[PDB]
Image (tube, rainbow over all chains, first blue to last red):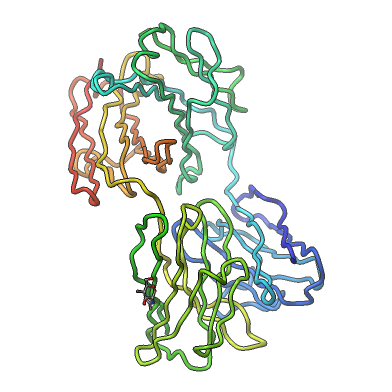
Length: 210
Length: 220
Ligand SMILES: *[C@@H]1O[C@H](CO)[C@@H](O)[C@H](O)[C@H]1NC(C)=O
């Protein structure tokens, strides 16, 4: 089976910047390759086919080249609408796609504002306690969130959710939710979330006492 | 210009049959291949198969025994059938046109159908307040929100003060909990000074269970 591998997995670039993303096939496929653009919640759009040929209507700042095993998609100067996930595709055989390259907007490092929320009394009636830690408006996307209950590091009882880049300021927000049973929540006192991020001089901890 | 429109049931239980249909408007089925492509949550596009003449389908080998693709030529429509679905068949399913060599890419595309396979029963969300507090006043800015928990299936909509409050609002993507139910939070950052003089209500709607919740969020 022929495999398509795209690099990098993730590109951060400024508006106006040039970007080149690559697609490598595990065996030669001559020029049987296409590139698609896909935005969240939407269908892919055809950009380039036969490795280097632009689909009609596609702007000239897009170009592609390559044949055999190494292929290139290039945008000579990015505009805001160009930020998206790009897929390459083998046009015959198993018609396999690459794993995709997400192109995100670069901007200055911005530290998160961190907030912690104890569970409501209403939720405690039901038998479950959710503790929520919010990281608001930060860049870059990477952040480490650790939960501590009575100073013990928690593992396997939290889930994170991250927003797409804000269309104006290009920042991220992140929620981490710690889920405990009512009995478990009520046998401990100190609840803390500790946030590590490139924008902070040192890890920030927000906490409360039950 | 040409539009591909899709319809068909997207909420399925294990072992049932996925049955989707793609309508083509602005063009005939003639002289072209018509294809289905799917995309699991957070994963890459996967070709399922395509057909030009009834009786000559071409399928992705790992799906051949479960997949039927067929043309309804009198209506210029084509359909996808996928039997004995499991949770692993959960994905957005796209239909697309594929033209004759040497012009082989997929174009145009349907808008996609979200398909969820689960044994989970339909359930309305519980809405809990994320109350603002003085140990959440980040330099004159407070944060507050609503926790929208244990619902199925997607989606829920969330607004604040009936759509009047829009600035500083972040409604996170739903996450699938280990219970098989979705959960979500919506938050907003407001001036602290406004906490004692301004009302904040999150409006939550879950149509699959006809659930409408207004929950006022007060400080503590
Ligand atoms: C698809 O499968 C369903 C159920 O298995 C069946 O009733 C139907 O005839 C098949 N074909 C179409 C076009 O729906």
